[PDB]
Image (tube, coloured by chain):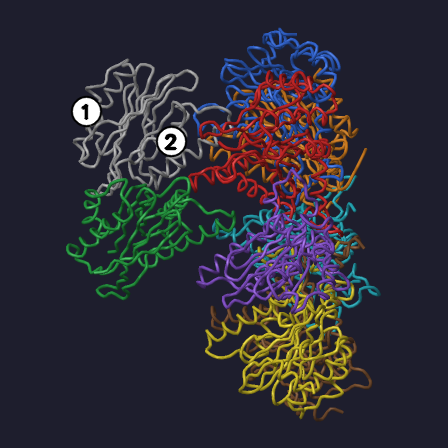
Amino acid sequence: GSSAGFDRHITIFSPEGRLYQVEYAFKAINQGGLTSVAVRGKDCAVIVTQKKVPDKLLDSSTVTHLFKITENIGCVMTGMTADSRSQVQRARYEAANWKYKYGYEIPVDMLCKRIADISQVYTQNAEMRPLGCCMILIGIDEEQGPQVYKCDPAGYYCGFKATAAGVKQTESTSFLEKKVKFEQTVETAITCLSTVLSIDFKPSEIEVGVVTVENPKFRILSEAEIDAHLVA
Amino acid sequence: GYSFSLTTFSPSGKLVQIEYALAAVAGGAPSVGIKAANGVVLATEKKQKSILYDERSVHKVEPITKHIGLVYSGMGPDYRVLVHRARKLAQQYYLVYQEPIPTAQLVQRVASVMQEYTQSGGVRPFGVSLLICGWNEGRPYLFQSDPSGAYFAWKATAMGKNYVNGKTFLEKRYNEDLELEDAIHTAILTLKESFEGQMTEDNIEVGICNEAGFRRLTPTEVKDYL
Amino acid sequence: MEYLIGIQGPDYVLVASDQVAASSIVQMKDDHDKMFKMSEKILLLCVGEAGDTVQFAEYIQKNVQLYKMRNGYELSPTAAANFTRRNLADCLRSRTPYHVNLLLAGYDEHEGPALYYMDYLAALAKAPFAAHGYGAFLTLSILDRYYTPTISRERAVELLRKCLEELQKRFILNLPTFSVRIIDKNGIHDLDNISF
Amino acid sequence: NQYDNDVTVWSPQGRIHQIEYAMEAVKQGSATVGLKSKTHAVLVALKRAQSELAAHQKKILHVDNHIGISIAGLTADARLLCNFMRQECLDSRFVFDRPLPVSRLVSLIGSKTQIPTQRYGRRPYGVGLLIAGYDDMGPHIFQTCPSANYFDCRAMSIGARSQSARTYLERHMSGFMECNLNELVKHGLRALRETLPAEQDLTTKNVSIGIVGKDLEFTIYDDDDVSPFLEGLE
Amino acid sequence: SYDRAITVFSPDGHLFQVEYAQEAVKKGSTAVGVRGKDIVVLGVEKKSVAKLQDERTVRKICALDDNVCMAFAGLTADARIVINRARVECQSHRLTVEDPVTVEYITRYIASLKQRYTQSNGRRPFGISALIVGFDFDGTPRLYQTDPSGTYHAWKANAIGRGAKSVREFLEKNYTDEAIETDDLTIKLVIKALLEVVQSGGKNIELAVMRRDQPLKILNPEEIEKYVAEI
Amino acid sequence: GYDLSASTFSPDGRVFQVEYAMKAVENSSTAIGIRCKDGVVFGVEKLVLSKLYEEGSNKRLFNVDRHVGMAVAGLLADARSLADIAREEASNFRSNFGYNIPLKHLADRVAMYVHAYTLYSAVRPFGCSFMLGSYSVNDGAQLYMIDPSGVSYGYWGCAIGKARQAAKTEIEKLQMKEMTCRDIVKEVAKIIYIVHDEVKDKAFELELSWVGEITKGRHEIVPKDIREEAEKYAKESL
Amino acid sequence: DRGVNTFSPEGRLFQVEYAIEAIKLGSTAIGIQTSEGVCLAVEKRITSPLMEPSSIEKIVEIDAHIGCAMSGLIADAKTLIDKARVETQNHWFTYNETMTVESVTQAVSNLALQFGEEDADPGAMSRPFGVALLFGGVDEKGPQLFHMDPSGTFVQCDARAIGSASEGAQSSLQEVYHKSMTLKEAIKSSLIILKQVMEEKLNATNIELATVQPGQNFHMFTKEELEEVIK
Amino acid sequence: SRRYDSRTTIFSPEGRLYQVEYAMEAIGHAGTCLGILANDGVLLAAERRNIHKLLDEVFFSEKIYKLNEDMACSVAGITSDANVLTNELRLIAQRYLLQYQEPIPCEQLVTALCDIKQAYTQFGGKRPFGVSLLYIGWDKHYGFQLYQSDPSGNYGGWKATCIGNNSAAAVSMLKQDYKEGEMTLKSALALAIKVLNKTMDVSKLSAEKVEIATLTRENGKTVIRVLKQKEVEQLIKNHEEE
Amino acid sequence: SIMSYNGGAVMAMKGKNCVAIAADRRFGIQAQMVTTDFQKIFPMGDRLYIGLAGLATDVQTVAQRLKFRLNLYELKEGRQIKPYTLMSMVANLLYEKRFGPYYTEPVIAGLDPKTFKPFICSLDLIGCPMVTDDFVVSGTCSEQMYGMCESLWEPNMDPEHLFETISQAMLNAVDRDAVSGMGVIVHIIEKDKITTRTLKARMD
């Protein structure tokens, strides 16, 4: 835990070779008090998130952590809200630009990498701080099938079978680990969230985004659609 | 952005930021490079934290050109930036000279990008060392580029976690006459010396470079070698 | 049209030029000096477009003098000629090109005498003798017929007079007086002006 | 200690010390009063003098034919802002061939002075202003601040001990609309004299007046020209 | 681009950076300039004179033009930059006014450049002081002195660098009309003034004179030795 | 000093500089926004610090577009520049696509601009929170609120200022979904008068503006007669 | 550490206050305005006998009808002096008339607060000027005297004393100056005050003096003239 | 941001530049380089620090760089910095040749790199180059020459000099043994080995631990050449006999 | 035309393990001859030469700029440049001025630094390379050179035969071109030697 000079204020190397500022940005992701779970199936990919509206006057329809990047790419953000929205906007811009110059839809792994590259710059440049959010992307690849990718504040990204983010990240990973060692995929995801939250939420308590092989277009399940999986 | 240097000389004449970037490298996962008579091998630990990480998704051993490949120890997202830069430098060279860039000319250009982040304004050095291998003029080449931007040509070396033990192991085992196929074995064995538990063909990654070019061994091939 | 002429000998370079400064149909000056001293043993004769000639020549002169001040020793004739060409060539494709024709004469301790020819497109050529302007057309052949590599300076002055006399009777322009200078190992020496 | 050096550094109480320090500059300046009736807008300022052999510092500047100002604080900044105001008025007359409405000009000042209070290395303008003008909406008296805030008032006072003038201003503001030119100028003078020391009094040396009304271009009265207004004060 | 203010005012109106630049001049080798009747002499100490060093490469007395030369004290690297700037300015002046610059004119230029570096963003002041000598077109000898702050004065005899005060005290009580009567005497004064600080008198001094019209001249070891024997 | 710059995260992952800017909005007058069945109503407890100020000075209600209104809280200078930014956005949108900018889009754009001042040491976060209200036949009634961090949310009822924790409970007890602009103007006025402190923060004025079917989609200040009634029904019912 | 544009708790710019402190260490300059004209007198403050007294210029000609007396960091003044010189010539070129003293002072005073280190461009000042000026000239309003300090504040004065003895000299100024005062008396009174506040024995070499009267151009006093008034 | 600025190019209270002084500390720890100038040539001799058995040899030399047809240099201190400077000297020499169609005189080249080094000390806010160079060259104005420059941007011509580890010792040893005008390349080379035997604390010198370029004239052509190991071995042998 | 302003002819010929490069020596402005020994062929290695024809000023500039780049290239990489690589370097250099090109059509002749394999090529003003196995011509009398080369060139000629072939090609080709002549310089590049000869030519 050594420290010298301004190695805890700006993104510079500390005595042990660590980047404290980047590590602090990972703690900022848990400040929102939410947890996200993405599960990759055999022919589908689902993203479940904790929908909390503790205010009553708030318009529940405007409260969501699931965003549509492209027609076939959806994502779930975790962490600082404002930072998340800017990253979602950046991803959308990157995706549209990719198609405009290359002639085809950007692959999920390429989009995730592009966002991670941008995040890396913040860990090397001292003038600006890293974003306090986490991005999880899901989409159907035409050659590889269902895809689940996640990048963070450190600029690190990877492909996953199933992965989580948020306050109960360590607990969601332990639940999904045993399961990996459509309907089941959606169920497993919801289960993982419910298991680590101990609440068994209703249809209006969570959000669901999915992409299947048959129906590649990113979709968001409604109250009646979420309840159906909850009743079973 | 800040226009003043974040790396500066201490009263002992050291550049601590670079010393600290090197600390990052030394805590990185292990990497090994061996230059055989008829090729070079690069081999690295890619143990993942869980079994949820799709190991096949991201690669630490990366091609730069038909004939050059890279591996690294230290900070993965810093590596990504370098890989992209080397790829752009190799293309730039090919567009001028219409011959694929010699390994040592790729190493000098990349190392130069590294030195600039020890002196330019507002930035920290790269928390990465590279091993670069290539084949050109019917000769195999292996180089290390560190965070200071210094480079060195090796017969064999190890970096990341447990490199000092690794090197001593390569002193004893390396010889010049050593063929590739054997080189590959002693690469994989240097990794074993510091590996946690049960080295599979999905938690190491291996690239080879020879006359045919540079390529990542397929997991199927790594298995045979294990 | 302005006239320049150079004759290189075994150990000297003889140069001459007309002294007429003209404005349309009238001679505004009859003692105009078209030679610019770049150094102790280097002369730069420049003719061409009004303005450009003096601007380019003085620009070169200032840099040559600066070179000597910065290092202690002077630039050699060859180096100075190439410096001049480079500068003239750089402006050729630029927005402001210098339309000047030059003759660079000089003497070097180890390289000996030298005479360079430079047209407005910055083509540099070393030569035993050369000329510029419309007068060169009527004098170059005279140089061809009488010039020998071992020509003495006294004989070179005689050769130059022949060229000047040819202009007097054949050339349509009124060039009654010429500046005559010589460069050897003792530096630049002014010779008696040749007038008619 | 660590929060009162930069304008871009928010303190823990939710304040910006640098903007507060820049407001102190206006409070150290010489007092000036601004009030309006129904057809006129006047400015009255106390001119300060470094020494007895020095001339009283200018405090009332010209902006346009329908706009005039009174400054307090850093004079260099006051001249800076004045130039900006003059240009804006000139631009309006060049483009639309009509005087720039006072209210619109005040908003431009607010925006211009707001910028420097958010950028690192920059500082707030250290000058307070009193703006008198006359457009299609009648006479106006605006007050610009160093923190880019501005208020539309019936009468205002800024500078050293301007609170006393403000107190007097509030007490006699009920009969300002119906006041006439001579009458309205007296009130300002009276309020301006309230901020002065018991011993000292307003004369034709330390007093400057600027008026702009329905049928009168913004004019400034100095020394001998302020005799008429001065004659009558109790 | 670096836009940080390095030279700023202190509580008692002091520019610390400029004073630190003057501290660097104090550690420089002593340099003495004496304005004679028909001659100008400059003399710098050689400090540590090694036997393996090429004497001609570390001369502290350079020429800015045919009539203008200068000796400096302080940061040698900084001096080189200033000297080059001045040389370029001398050729610029010679090209726009068709005349050799006056000593005061180039002194003014160097002083102005030094001041510019005490009120600019991202730069530090030049850590040198210079002695400028030469002759103007009319023939009158000149001697100027510039410092890091940018101020400059005309002198009769001045001394800069380590021991400037000591040499100044001796120069005041030794500079008269019967001390610069002849060229030799003027040179002796500078050598004698340089002997008050420079240790091991003899070859530890670099001398150079500038007589009217002719180019700068540099005295040789044996030529200086002879002068020392007469003193 | 972990709270000196916006480009510096503290050990527990917080950006204190942005939080300090939220403190500036916390110690300011309260403004309210209510989304009724056919429109939005804005009400601000304008604090009159001096009697010299003219009736209608330091307005905290702005018209950022023909169909959009803005109610702010916190540093007025910061709020004013944000209003100009909002106006620029609306204007730019119409020039690019040929029609009135949707409220949600306008709010998202302005929020991103606000979010841009919370990542660097070169600039400081905005010291103000504002509300955006608008009404159109193709969109219905929409109400959004943006704070110093840059988070933008849609609401049914919203409060910003020093008394927002008390005004929310008063807004809670109301059936705004079935209410109308004409009826919500009296409740807004009533609520503002309730949260307003007597002893502390004395002397205030009531600012009222609305946009909806009653005003044919145009945002404007509530009429004097209607405001009179609302204020008369607010004082009588308190 | 604070930036150059940092405000203090009393509402003042730290740097400008420190720049005003630097003016107190300068030489004493006196300016008196009469109906006959304006006279300027500043002490040269010679620190050594070898230093040439004519190389110390504390009073300069801005134009034919405008003179200037500086005090404080003399090197900083040069830049402001050139600006004033350019402003008057620019005014003459464009309007075919002479610029008024007030106008020239105003233009020069506008550069006072033009310094910073963040939003500035390649060529901006990193700190304020550390010098006080005295502008004396004659326009259509007759003889005029203006005083400008480092804060950018300029004001007309009947009599002003800047420099190290500013306080003591100002007291003698107000106790000896009247509206009917003549030029001859002003020149004498200023010299009488300068000699009383000078640490060195005032003479015809250690002081400068210039006058600007109706008709006559800016005129610097020669040694002879100076001596006559010293009796 | 003033807070994080290190303030690289400002003076200390004694009129010192600390970054330059600390850059110099770096160098005094680098591998020893020494230059000796003879009548018939000039030579550089450098301790190698790249010594590990698994290092490949692939390159001309570790620390000796050719700059143009007529000059070479060796460097001490921060290797990656030296790479920036050596590439810049090559660019400067080729700029000169392009303009004048002649090789750059050795002192003009040195001076022009040192201008780049002094600028880093005065403006821009970056740390200096942590490098000292020795340069050897032949030109038509001065013939055989040897220069040294340092991170301050200061340079000076020498008959013999040394930089890097134990330079102070090497210098006093060269002051004892170097014969002005009486030196031949054979004599120079001998002295190099003598001085290098004493500045290196490995007792046995070893021709693997040193690098020696010589620079001579043959038929109006400069010849720069790294001595091969045999020659160095012999050179070492020859010292043992003494 | 700008290319014929100064005149000049350059040609390269391939032989059995040897290359030949020749050029005229005339430097003239329009119809007037100025000198008779203007260099058009420049060395770019022991066995690598570049011939340049076209505007004299551009001939000198390109040659000098190419030398600048080659020198730096040979300092960076520690080896002699290969003939093919030089061609690309020149092409890249010529293509940089795509819309304001140097008026010169270069011809390269040499042998590989390590394999000593004959190589000849020609590039147009904008830098479009053309590698041939027989010969390449460039200049004001290219048509005449084509005729001569096409009928005189034979495969696998030895050093002596190659010299005679290129000499006869150039000599007879420049005699039908008014702006090309005043001497001919021939360079014979072999594995262990380079032979430079000046032919007996017409001086009119």
- Look at the image and give the colour of chain G: yellow
Judge left or right: residue D164 versus residue B94.
right
- Is A165 rendered above or below residue F74? above
- Look at the image and give the colour of chain D: brown
Residue that sits furthest to the right in the current view: F199
Q: Quadrant of residue E64?
A: bottom right
Judge left or right: residue H36 versus residue D97.
right
- Look at the image and give the colour of chain E: purple
E185 or F150: nearer the eye?
E185
- The chain painted green is C
What SS does tag 1 mark? helix
| Residue I91: assigned label | 2
Q: Chain of mark 1?
A: I
In the image, what residue type sits under mark 2?
A: Ala
What SS does tag 2 mark? helix
- Look at the image and give the colour of chain B: blue
Q: Chain of mark 2?
A: I
| Structural distance between the alpha carbons of marks 2 and 1 | 27 Å
- The chain painted cyan is F
| Residue I147: assigned label | 1
- Look at the image and give the colour of chain A: orange
Q: Position of residue G177 (x, y in %)?
A: 71, 88
Query: Callout 1 environment at 10 Å: few (<14), some (14 to 19), or many (20+)?
Result: few
- Is B64 rendered above or below residue I103? above
Q: Position of residue C140 (x, y in %)?
A: 21, 46
Foreground: disc 2 or disc 1: 1
E186 or E74: nearer the eye?
E186
Query: Callout 2 environment at 10 Å: few (<14), some (14 to 19), or many (20+)?
Result: many
